[PDB]
Image (spheres, grey):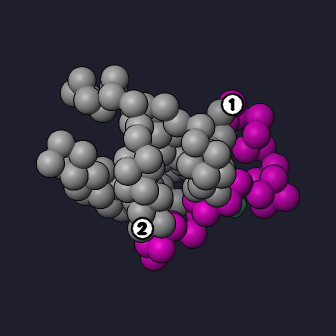
Amino acid sequence: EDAMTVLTPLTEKDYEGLKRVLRSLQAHKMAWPFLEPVDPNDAPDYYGVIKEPMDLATMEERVQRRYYEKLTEFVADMTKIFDNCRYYNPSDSPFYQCAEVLESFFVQKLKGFKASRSH
Ligand SMILES: CC(=O)Nc1ccc(CN2CCOCC2)cc1
């Protein structure tokens, strides 16, 4: 990551952009498994294996409360969603496929956000 991403504080204008990025992911057709925390009734062994769970509703709460100080911290939480999914599920599962698709989409939107900060 470049120096702006790591070290430039998130301004109010930056936060409006983060809200838009998040809403785009929440509206994606392949985002359904990630919208809310993993349901322990459906996955009884999940919280024993995955030590730092993450989901898009937890990220929305954090954005609203201005939890993030630097872009790198927002990117780290998002990346945790996808990394947790690829570690827990096998490579041939529909969950794994959704992570592949949605991470690619996130990278496209994140590049757009970074461009709009510098110009
Ligand atoms: C985002 C995420 O990883 N979700 C998730 C949801 C349920 C399970 C539990 N299993 C999966 C396949 O077998 C039936 C139930 C595992 C992972």
Nearer-N-terminus badge (1/2): 2
Secondary structure found at label 1: loop
Looking at the rendering, which quadrant does residue 84 occupy?
top right
Question: Is 6 placed left or right of 114 in the picture?
Answer: right
- When the figure is inspected, residue 12 is found, relative to residue 24, above or below; the finding is above
Residue 24 is tagged as: 2
Q: Main secondary structure of the magenta part?
A: loop
Q: Residue at x 38, y 50 (%)?
A: 13
Q: Classify the position of ligand 1 by quadrant: top left, top right, bottom left or bottom right.
A: bottom right
What's the CA distance linking mark 1 and mark 2?
27 Å
Give 7 or 24, whichever is nearer the viewer: 7
Look at the numbered disc 2 and give the secondary structure of its residue: helix
Question: Which residue corresponds to the image point at 42% horizontal and 67% vertical from the top-left?
Answer: 24
Tell me residue 59's x, y (percent): 59, 49
Chain part drawn in magenta:
25-51
Amino acid marked by disc 2: Ser
| Residue assigned mark 1 | 51
Q: Position of residue 79 (x, y in %)?
A: 45, 41
Identity of the residue drawn at 61% across and 63% down: 35
- Which amino acid does the dot numbered 1 rest on? Lys
Location of residue 95 with respect to 82 vertically, above or below: below
- Quadrant of the image containing the N terminus: top left
Magenta span has 42? yes
User: In this orientation, does residue 86 appear?
Assistant: no
Percent of width and height locating residue 40 = 81, 53
